[PDB]
Length: 60
Length: 222
Image 1: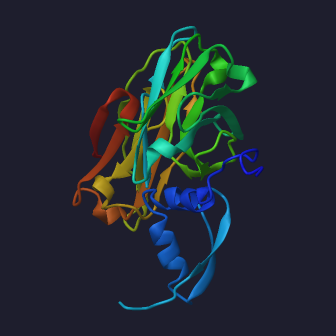
Image 2: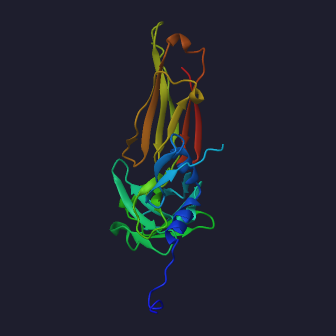
């Protein structure tokens, strides 16, 4: 019955943040060059956090 | 990715001067922008920084109260207004991009512009006078004789000296400038050539002084 006492928060705020940093001019070429060699690579994003990146399907 | 800076020149001590820096190739509206100066021959000096939204400006202690930084994201420009200039402010100023995007804490510079030179000396700007250092008529028949140009009485630095618009490069020595007693600069550019080439090939030195928009072509004859 005490569900109203808890605070509200954004669940996908982290994913939305990672998306907003991927819309910068560039940053897509960064990931593309990183994944040019293998299908998985750690990429340093322009916001500083380093994230793991997968190429799960090669259609080109 | 490019940062093109403009607004440099010579300004008397105590007066003002505004530098601008335009950006192209990245989302400028999300990167903090730094101004970093470097005295001639000395190390790097941090000047100022402005956050991505433009509501957070930080200045170095040596320029506090005098300089003021501003930005315009609709045109991708950063402006640094410097009034009440001392002679210690004479330096080359770069605008630089902050490595980390969309933050209120500034980390470092990853993309640097070319720079704008700012000279404070009370002396005025004068274009150079070019005098011919003509080859001697004693030169042996062989004979490896030498000629050149004397670029005298110019301010400020630098001047660029070429020979035959770049067609002559071998044996060319352009000396570093010296500060004459008049407060103006002067250098010499010499070329050693076969003596059998004099009177056959035209020798012309090209002197360029950008601060005064001076372009001189000096023909050297015996």
